[PDB]
Length: 50
Length: 49
Image (cartoon, rainbow over all chains, first blue to last red; front, side, top):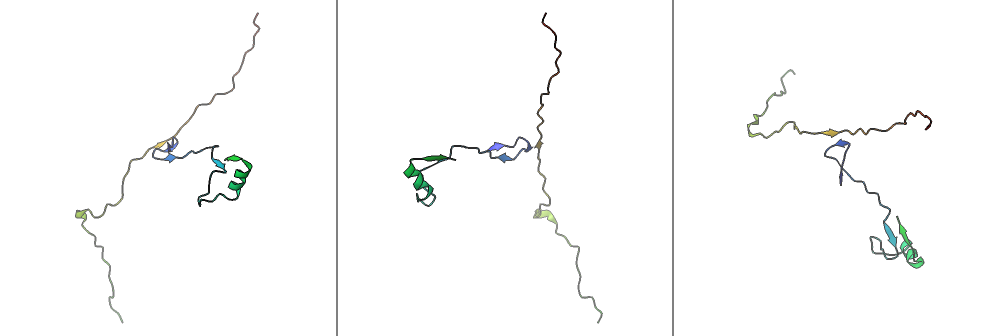
């Protein structure tokens, strides 16, 4: 959390800018599955940077 | 059929047990930010000789 420099002094602002969220064949879904996009990434030996 | 049927009172509690707080005060502050920009210059050219 960061302070809100312009505005109320008791405001906390979230500024999350990331280009490094990896999706790959070794990462599973919240339900534990690795189907669909994940399976194709595993077969193609590819990973995504979201 | 003419009778007084109802009434309402202007009764209040004595807040000596401080059951009620009423309105609240809190101290606050706001911040404003004013950055100063640069502007294009004006130039007077002259020869170096």
